[PDB]
Image: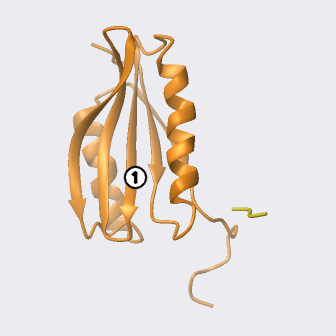
Chain colours: A yellow, B orange
Amino acid sequence: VLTX
Amino acid sequence: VPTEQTVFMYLPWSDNLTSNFYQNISDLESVVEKNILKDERIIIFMCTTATKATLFELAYENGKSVHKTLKNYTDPAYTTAEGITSILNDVQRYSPTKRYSMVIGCHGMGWIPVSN
């Protein structure tokens, strides 16, 4: 799961 | 003749969020479809690669959202002050308004300097  | 506000969406190269940015633009277009831009313009700068970018307007025409391409860029210097100034001067030339706002999409690391 990716974040900025 | 909208003259009140330009919303500038600024999407410089992010390495791996490009697809997310396209969905952000699609989501914002769903709002343009409701004919809310009588006094305002939406202008978008987006890097499609690290070295290629486009400037375009989202507008409402014949009952629909539409992309009006304003210009393209080769090797824009978007990590430099001069490059950012030149892009913002393009935004102002294409969209002369009383007010401007900026929406910046990318990876963030607060105040941390690039050079550590």
Q: Is residue B16 above or below residue B46?
A: below
Secondary structure type for disc 1: strand
Q: Is residue B116 above or below residue B11?
A: below
Query: Foreground residue, B27 or B57?
Result: B27
Q: Quadrant of the N terminus of chain B?
A: top left
Query: Foreground residue, B13 or A2?
Result: A2
Chain for numbered disc 1: B
Residue B86 location, quadrant:
bottom left
Q: Residue furthest bottom?
A: B116
| Residue shown at 31% from the left, 39% from the top | B56
Q: Quadrant of the C terminus of chain B?
A: bottom right
Q: Is residue B7 left or right of residue B77?
A: right
Mark 1 crowdedness (10 Å alpha carbons): few <14, some 14-19, many ≥20: many
Q: Is residue B76 above or below residue B20?
A: below
| Residue B89, percent from left and from top | 27, 47
Q: Amino acid at mark 1?
A: Met
Residue B51 location, quadrant:
bottom left
Residue B61 location, quadrant:
top left
| Residue shown at 51% from the left, 35% from the top | B26
| Residue shown at 38% from the left, 70% from the top | B50
Location of mark 1 (residue): B46
| Residue B71, percent from left and from top | 20, 46
| Residue shown at 39% from the left, 15% from the top | B64
| Residue B42, percent from left and from top | 41, 30
Q: Is residue B108 above or below residue B70?
A: below
